[PDB]
Amino acid sequence: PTINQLVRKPRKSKVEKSDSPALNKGYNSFKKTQTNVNSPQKRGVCTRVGTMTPKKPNSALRKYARVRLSNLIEVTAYIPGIGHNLQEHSVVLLRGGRVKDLPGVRYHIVRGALDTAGVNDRKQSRSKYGTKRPKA
Amino acid sequence: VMTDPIADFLTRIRNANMVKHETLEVPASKIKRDIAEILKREGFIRDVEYIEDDKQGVIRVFLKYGKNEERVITNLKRISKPGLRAYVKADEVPKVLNGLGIAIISTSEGVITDKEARAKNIGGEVIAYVW
RNA sequence: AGUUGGUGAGGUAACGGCUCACCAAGGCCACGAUGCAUAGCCGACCUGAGAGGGUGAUCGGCCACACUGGGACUGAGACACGGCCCAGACUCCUACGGGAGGCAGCAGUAGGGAAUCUUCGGCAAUGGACGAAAGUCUGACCGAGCAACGCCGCGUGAGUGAAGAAGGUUUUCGGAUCGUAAAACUCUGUUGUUAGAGAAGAACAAGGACGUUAGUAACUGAACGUCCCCUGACGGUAUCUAACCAGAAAGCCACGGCUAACUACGUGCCAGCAGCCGCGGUAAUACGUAGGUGGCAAGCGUUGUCCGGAUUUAUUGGGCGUAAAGCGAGCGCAGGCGGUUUCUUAAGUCUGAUGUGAAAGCCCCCGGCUCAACCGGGGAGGGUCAUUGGAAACUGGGAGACUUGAGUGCAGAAGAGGAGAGUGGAAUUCCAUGUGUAGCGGUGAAAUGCGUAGAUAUAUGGAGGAACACCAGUGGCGAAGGCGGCUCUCUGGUCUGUAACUGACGCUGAGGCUCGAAAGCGUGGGGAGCAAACAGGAUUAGAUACCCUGGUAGUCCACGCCGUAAACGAUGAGUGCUAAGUGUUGGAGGGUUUCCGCCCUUCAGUGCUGCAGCAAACGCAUUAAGCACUCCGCCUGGGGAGU
RNA sequence: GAGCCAGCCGCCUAAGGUGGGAUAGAUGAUUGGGGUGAAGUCGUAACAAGGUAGCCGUAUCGGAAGGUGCGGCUGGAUCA
C-alpha cells in the first residue's frame, strides 16, 4: 500500500497459538485466577484406564488413561511402552507431546517417573520408558 | 496530473533506450538540464543541446550505443520520490555496483555525483541511480 | 461543577484552586479524552545478515510497600522495615475485670508446586554507628557447608606388539568381522594413598621515644614527618618435595528418506513406533532383542519457552484478470500530493565547536593467575538531546512575473440523455350481428378441456389494457443501473474550431450525502396477454418435477419504503512515454475537384490482427495485464461462517 | 493576676448499615445449530448437453436433496 496508508494504519500480525494449553494453568487458588505458569509438566490422578481404537488406515488397540490435572481441567492422555501398572486412583505425571494416529489426545504420561512403573524388559533405549540399567 | 517530472524524465530515457532509437525531446527546466549535464560527462549521453521558445522546453538528448550495437546506459531508477523524500549523510553516501555505477545527489552546494560527495563530506538528498 | 479563569483572604522550605468567600461560564476531546484490561521503570541479556523481535532473573540506578485501612508526634531529615494511637481479621494468656503479637532481615518449619540449600565460623580486611582514645555493636560482610544447575581446564594410561590366540556374530561353509583389539615385554604418576616442608591476604589506630611549623609570656597540646612496638575466622588451607601402584575411574542417543551410520533372529494390521512422510496381514535395514557402525562424551536424551529459517505483515522486502483480494457508481468538508521562473527567509536538510549520554557489560589494545573461564588498566559506541557558527541545491514560509494544466468567451456538430402533456397503427382477447355445420384444441403417444343453450371458421362494428413489426447496425447517448412508435413545453452533458479573457484556481478523496436492475412491502387506481402458489390431465417403481388444459398475487400507473445481483471487461482513478496494419460513428483542415462521389494531414470514441515487453501457463499489447509517479480500497491455508 | 492544662462542645474523615442501579464468572428442567464417527435406511441435485445447460439475487413451495416464477452472466457442449 501507499506509505501514507501504513502511516494511518497499524499493519498488524497473526499471533500464533499453543500446542498444549493444559500446561499453562488457568489458576485456581485461592480465588481461581490467571495464567503465567508455562511448566514443562504437571500431574494428576488417573480417573479411568482403558483401550481405544485408532482411525483408518492404521489398526490397533491403543492403551489410554483419562486423568484430571491438578489445575482443575480434564485431559485424556496416553501411555507408552509394553504393559503398565496404571489403574483407577493413581497419581502420575504428564509429558507434552501429540500423537497423530489417534484423535482426542495431545498429552502422554512419562514412564517410571512417578507412581507408574518403568517398562520391565527393554535393554536398548531405557532412557525413555524409565528402565534402570541391568547390572546382572 | 504530472506530479513528479524527474521520474518522468528518467522513464522517458528508459523507454526510448529499450526500443533503441536515438533522439529524445523533453520539456526543459532548471534541474533537468543539470542532471542531463551530469549524465553527459560520465560517458552516458552522447550529446545534448538546449532549445527554448517562450516556455519550458526543450532538452534534446542523443543517446549513445556501443559499436557492436549494445546499450551503455543499462537502467535507471528514482530514489527520493515525492511522498517519501530520501536523504543521506556523508557517512552513508550510496555507491552503486562497487563503482561501476553512479548516483546523483543534491548537495547544499549543488548537484554532483557521489564520489564528489565523499571527497567533500556532505550529505543531501539523492535523486537517482544509474548503471 | 473546585471543574477552567479572576478578585481577595488563609496557608506551605516554597509558586499554585493547595483551601476558603465572591464573580464569569469555561476546560479537554478524531493528532484517541473517558473507560476497560495487562505490567513496576532503566543500564542490560537472547536472537538476527540487518532492519528488528522477545525478555527486565544474578550486578548497578530509581520508584513504591511493611498483617489490611486510617492519623500524627519527636525530629534537620518520617507520615517511620524490628516506633506510637484508632478500627478490622487471625494466634496466645488470664483470677474475666483485662493484656500481648506481626521473618516481604539471616538461618529453619508447615502449605502450594514439575522444581530450588546449613537453624555454620569470625570482626583478621573493607564499610558503617557511638566514643577524646582504648573499645563495644555490626546475619552489612568475609569465609565455611550442600546441589554436575552453568561455564572453563584435566584423567580413566603409553611404546613394541599377527596370517590373527579363545569367544561372539555371520557365512555360498571357502571364510569375514569384532582386531594390535587382546596377549607378552618396556615405561610413566597428571591422578590416589602416605610422610615431611609450608606462605600472600597485615595496612593500621593505640603506646613509646625524636623533630619541624603556626600560636603565645611561656609549655601542655595541634597539624604532619622518622624509628621500636603490637593483631588471622579462613587454616596447617593453597603449595613444594620423597615413596608406591596400570593399578580404584564410561556412559548416553541413534542407524527407511530429510540425516552421518546394516545385517541376522524373533512377532505377522496383534504387539507396537514415529517430528513429517508413513511402517506392522509369513522372508520387515521402520516393531523387539542380538551383533556391528556413527555422533557426543562426564555427560547424554525428552518435555516446556523466545528468536531464526518465514520475503508467512514485505521500510530495507509481497500482492489484487481466472488462484484470497477493486467498494455497484457518483458529489465531495477534513486530509495526502502538486505546473514554470526572479528575489527572499532559513522551519525541514547537510556541516563545525562545546556540554552531556554513571559504574559494571558487548567490542579493541595491553596486563596478571602454570593456560582457560575470571580478574586489572586504558580506549572507542550509543541522542531522535541542549547551546552556539556556517551553506543555500532540494521541500516548506514571504513579495513577485508567466501560460502549456484547468476554466471562461466567441463559432459550429451529433445523440433510443431526463422529466411533464397529448397522440398513431398492427396484434391478442371479450362483446354485438350475418353465414355455417360437427367438431375444435393438444401430444413422443394420449388424456383433461370448449362444443347441437350452435363450437372452431368467417365477415362488420364496438370495448379495454399492454408492448412498439420493418429502419436495426462488434451503431448512438449516459458515471453506473440503463435508454428504441410520433409530436410539443421545461432541462443536463459531450466533441471540433478560434485563442478574446483569469492566472495553477489542480488530482485523489477516510467519515457524510445522492443515485441505485429484478424480486419484495404500504396506500389508492387499473387489469388484455403471461405466470410463482394452486387444480385437473398425463409419464413413472414412486414424481408433491420436466409435458398438456385452467388459474390467484405479480407484471402497469402516482406517492412513499427496502438498498441488494455473475450490479462483469470478475480489469479503482488522474497523468505522461513506447512499431505497425485493418474497418467503423462524429468532426476540422489541404490537393484533385461537379470530391457532395477520391487522395493526404489531424482530433475524438469505437472493434479485429500483431512487434518489443510482461505473464506460472491461458494470453495482453496506444482502449496494456508494458514503462513510471500521486491518492484511495482490499488480502495473508481450507472448513467452522459472512454463523 | 497573666499564662498554661484536665473536662466539654464544633468542622473534617477510615471501618460499618441501608437503597437503587452497573458489570464479570459459574450454574439450570428444556432447547438451536456444527464437527466427527466402521458397516444403516431414503433418493440421485452437480461433474459429458450428467439425460429438464449451469450459476447469482430474490419470492413461494416441499421428508430431503431440490422445483417453480422474474431479472442477470458465459466461466455453455452442439450449431446453422
Image: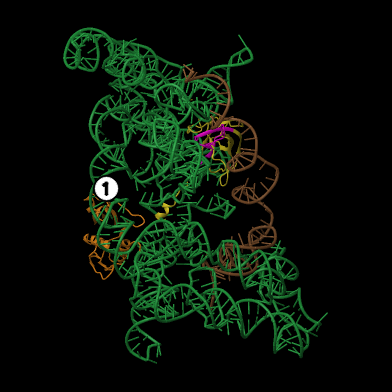
Chain colours: A yellow, B orange, C green, D brown
User: For the magenta stretch, what is the residue range?
Assistant: A16-45
The answer to whether residue C593 is above or below residue C497 is below
SS class of the residue under badge 1?
Answer: helix
Q: Residue at image x 25%, y 66%?
A: B61
Magenta span: predominant SS is loop
- Does the magenta portion include A28? yes
**Residue C583 position by quadrant:** bottom left
Q: Quadrant of the N terminus of chain A?
A: bottom left
- Does the magenta portion include A109? no
Looking at the image, which is closer to me, A131 or A100?
Answer: A100
The answer to whether residue C502 is above or below residue C118 is below
Q: Amino acid at mark 1?
A: Asp
The answer to whether residue A19 is above or below residue D1 is below
Q: Position of residue A51 (x, y in %)?
A: 60, 38
Q: Which residue is mark 1?
A: B91
Q: Residue at image x 57%, y 38%?
A: A75
Q: Position of residue C604 (x, y in %)?
A: 41, 74
* Structural crowding at the residue carrying mark 1, measured as other residues with C-alpha within 10 Å and reported as few (<14), some (14–19) or many (≥20): few
Q: Position of residue C174 (x, y in %)?
A: 40, 37
Looking at the image, which is closer to me, C81 or C25?
Answer: C25
Check the residue under mark 1 and report the chain it is in. B
Q: Position of residue B22 (x, y in %)?
A: 26, 68
Looking at the image, which is closer to me, C408 or C147?
Answer: C408
- In the rendered structure, the answer to whether residue B6 lies left or right of residue B119 reads right
